[PDB]
Length: 76
Image 1 (spheres, rainbow, N blue to C red):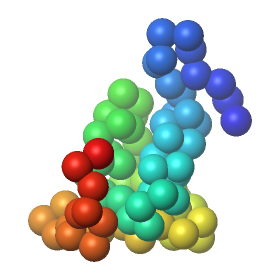
Image 2 (cartoon, helix red, strand yellow; image 1 turned 90 degrees about the horizontal axis):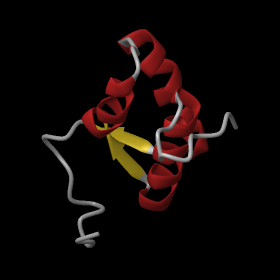
Image 3 (tube, one colour; image 1 turned 180 degrees about the horizontal axis):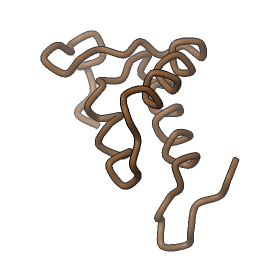
């Protein structure tokens, strides 16, 4: 719950919360779209794993990116 800035620059926490919400809506998240936003920070795969576990527990399946179509009924 560590708030983002007014410039829409988010924190690791906020990005976590973004991705969380997105995954919660979809039921899925590709690993690299998750990594994408975390590229603003320095997040290793180890730390990512912790987030993946988190997401999984909330209700988000993490797919790769080379696959995706269960959620592809939305343009955006």
